[PDB]
Amino acid sequence: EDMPVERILEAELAVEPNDPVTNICQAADKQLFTLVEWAKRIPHFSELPLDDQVILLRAGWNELLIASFSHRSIAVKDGILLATGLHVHRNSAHSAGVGAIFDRVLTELVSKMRDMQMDKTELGCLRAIVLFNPDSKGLSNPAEVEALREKVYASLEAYCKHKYPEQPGRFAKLLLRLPALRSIGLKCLEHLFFFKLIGDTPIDTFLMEMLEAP
Amino acid sequence: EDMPVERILEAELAVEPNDPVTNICQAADKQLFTLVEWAKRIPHFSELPLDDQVILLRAGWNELLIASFSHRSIAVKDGILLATGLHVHRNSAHSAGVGAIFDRVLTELVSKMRDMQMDKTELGCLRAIVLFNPDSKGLSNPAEVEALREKVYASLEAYCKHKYPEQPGRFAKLLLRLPALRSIGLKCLEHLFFFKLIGDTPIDTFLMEMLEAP
Amino acid sequence: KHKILHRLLQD
Amino acid sequence: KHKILHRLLQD
Ligand SMILES: CC(=C/C=C/C(C)=C/C(=O)O)/C=C1\CCCc2cc(C)ccc21
Ligand SMILES: CC(=C/C=C/C(C)=C/C(=O)O)/C=C1\CCCc2cc(C)ccc21
């Protein structure tokens, strides 16, 4: 109850109008600041205790940013568009040693989004579901987070079937990209910890903080 | 089209009526044989080319087995029931160094299944969706696999809403456990590769083959 | 490759 | 801990 897709869409429209790895890390750090503002625009999020707000963002920031640049890259030929306005071509990513993860983003996320023409409302809702992850460890009231999530996909399904009546399986199709997002999110984090370990690849303060423990 | 939940349920009913790690590995090897038979009972699966059948099972066996023993453990206090008829108590898993992954299985999977009273038909369908993973690399016809998956969750949603009319968000709730299954599946595989690397912990032939490359 | 799996699927 | 994140959320 009280989870209008209009507010979710607004949050998306409000936050967004040579080693490629380094460029990706700078873009991620950059978007981390924008991510917090996006979250504050998601209904009832800011109403949760500060401690749980931190846990939720800590637990889903990687998937949240990935979903975002992936959808942004729908208009891209063979690459990804970073928030900084730079483009990472497949060859560039390949030549940097990150071709494997790059190919997964394109095939499992970008390509699928483009083919089904995922819109900004749907993207917003999927990220809202990810943000409200009831499995996040440390939550003082997991039931409360579970409630918000249920309200999001409840509004999302309503959005679909209504906008896209001719596609009864659209709602499920949207939800079925979450497993790929989870796996891809995990691999990207592994690469980030390796970059931090090796020493090379400058990592900014906010991104570094997210890599911090726990 | 042509994906009756009745057949899916039948497949589930047909395949199922001291270091805990070693017991878990023996149970997994054991279930790998049963898994192939379960797959053959899933409509249209055996109709796919041998090469794609292999890719699908190779790509989802870990998640398929995890979903299964997790649902089987619903009647368990604080532990998991293995197919071999042995029970792995939380303390036992903890004392073996696998308490973390063990806690995730219980909290993210077992507990959630029990609370919503996930039935055998629903479990069967969720596994069928996992089996028909269109993102599996190597597929000669990914579109064909995507088609079967869509037909499964199409029948699953029909099953729900009809059996559980009073729970409109049940279908989505079921699908929303797939992300946890994916993450948990990945961590368990990591533990398995470490067990194989260390040398200790006997690993049988079928399980070993699944650890093999690619 | 995938000795075991292939044999089982064929049967 | 989580210096940056807390400050941003509070603002
Ligand atoms: C964790 C992460 C965050 C991305 C933030 C960005 C780039 C946001 C944006 O530009 O909108 C992604 C990584 C993290 C580092 C590895 C990596 C490699 C490829 C090919 C693609 C993505 C990633
Ligand atoms: C990959 C895997 C397969 C399990 C198969 C079983 C045990 C099937 C069954 O008994 O029905 C699970 C593992 C693999 C090894 C690590 C592990 C640890 C815990 C606490 C639980 C599960 C696992």
Image (spheres, coloured by chain):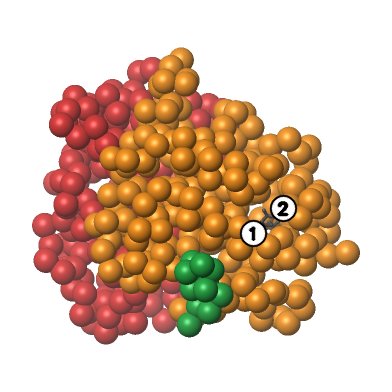
Chain colours: A orange, B red, C brown, D green
Tell me residue A128's x, y (percent).
45, 48
Quarter of image, res B1: top left
Mark 1 Cα-neighbour bin, 10 Å: few <14, some 14–19, many ≥20 = many
Residue farthest right in this picture: A18
Q: Residue at x 31, y 25 (%)?
A: B155
- Relative horizontal placement of residue A168, taking residue B19 as reference (left or right): right
Residue wearing tag 2: A83
In this rendering, would A148 be left or right of B140?
left
Q: Where the C terminus of chain B falls, by quadrant?
A: bottom right
**Residue closer to the observer: B82 or A123:** A123
Chain ID of residue with mark 2 = A
Which numbered dot is residue A81? none
Answer with the quarter of the image where residue A55 lies. Answer: bottom left
Pointer 1 and pointer 2: residues touching (CB < 8 Å)? yes
Tell me if residue B93 can be seen. Answer: yes
Q: Is mark 2 within 8 Å of ligand 1?
A: yes
Residue on which the image places disc 1: A31
Q: Is mark 1 within 8 Å of ligand 1?
A: yes
The residue at 47%/20% (across/down) is: A164
Look at 36% across and 52% down and name the residue there: A44
Q: Please, what is the three-letter code of the amino acid marked with disc 2?
A: Ala
Q: Position of residue A200 (x, y in %)?
A: 77, 78
Looking at the rendered structure, the secondary structure element under dot 1 is helix
